[PDB]
Each structure stands twice: as structure tokens, then as C-alpha cells.
Amino acid sequence: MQLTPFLILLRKTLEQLQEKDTGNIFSEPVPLSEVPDYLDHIKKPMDFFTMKQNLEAYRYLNFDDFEEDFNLIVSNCLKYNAKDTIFYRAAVRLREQGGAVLRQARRQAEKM
Ligand SMILES: COc1cc2c(cc1NS(=O)(=O)c1ccc(C#N)cc1)c(C)cc(=O)n2C
């Protein structure tokens, strides 16, 4: 029963957020093989594959918690990376574009 309007809204919204990540930079966890110090800085890694995992395990009880996980993708990236990096620039753009997606989707999560 992923067939409830709240859960269909989260699935839709997650798709729309991944669409804004045009480089697929945030599609999967930051790889510790390529990035060995990541956990020295970042206490709670997050990425869209993890969010999708969470969604399907009914771990998102409300829209707030879903939105907090998206914000972690962005805030982690801005925290870890220098300003002059593809990653940081991507996160700034994702914050801007994804904030708008979330604005609209929250409107619908209220109506429930
Ligand atoms: C999911 O792949 C990554 C995501 C990353 C980071 C690194 C990777 N992987 S990587 O180190 O293999 C890599 C290095 C350079 C580019 C470019 N351009 C892309 C990936 C790094 C270094 C930081 C980061 O915030 N994110 C989101």
C-alpha cells in the first residue's frame, strides 16, 4: 500500500527533486572509497537513493521529516565542499530549485 495520497505525493515529490539534480550528483551515497574523510565532517549522510529506500519502508510519517532529509543532502554538501567546486555549486542550485518543489508539495500535504 504505497497507494495512499500522502505516499504518492512523497513519491512524486522525490522524482521532481531528483529531476532537479541533473548531474545525478546526489542520486547515491557519497562514496567513502573516493572520499575517505567524509564522516569526520558529516554526521548524517543523505542522498536520494536513501530517501527512496526510506519512502518504500514507510519511514516517512509526515512531510516535515521528508523535507528534513532533502535539506540534509544540500546542507551536508555545502558544509563538506569548498565553494569553488562542482558539488557546492550543484547544491546551491538544488536548494534553489528544490525549495520551490517542496513549497508546492507542502501545500498539498496540508490538504490531507
Ligand atoms: C556520488 O558521487 C560523489 C558525490 C560527492 C562527492 C564525490 C562523489 N564521487 S567521486 O569522488 O567519485 C567524484 C569526483 C569528481 C566528480 C566530478 N566532477 C564526480 C564524482 C564529493 C567529493 C562531495 C560531495 O558532496 N558529493 C555529493
Image: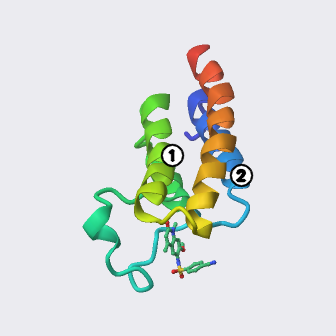
Q: Nearer the viewer, residue 84 or 94?
A: 84
Relative to 43, say whether 15 is above or below: above
- Furthest residue to the bottom? 33
Residue at x 30%, y 64% (from the top left corner): 41
Q: Position of residue 12 (x, y in %)?
A: 68, 41
How far apart are labels 1 and 2 at the CA level? 12 Å
Q: Residue at x 57, y 41 (%)?
A: 2
Looking at the rendered structure, the secondary structure element under dot 2 is helix
Question: Helix, strand or loop at disc 1?
Answer: helix
Q: Position of residue 110 (x, y in %)?
A: 57, 16
In the image, ligand 1 is in what quadrant? Answer: bottom right
Percent from the top left, x then y, of residue 50?
A: 47, 58
What residue sits right under mark 2 in the picture?
A: 20
Q: Toward the viewer: 28 or 100? A: 100
Residue 84, image x, y percentages: 57, 66
Circle 1 sits on which residue?
A: 70
83 to 31, vertically: above or below: above
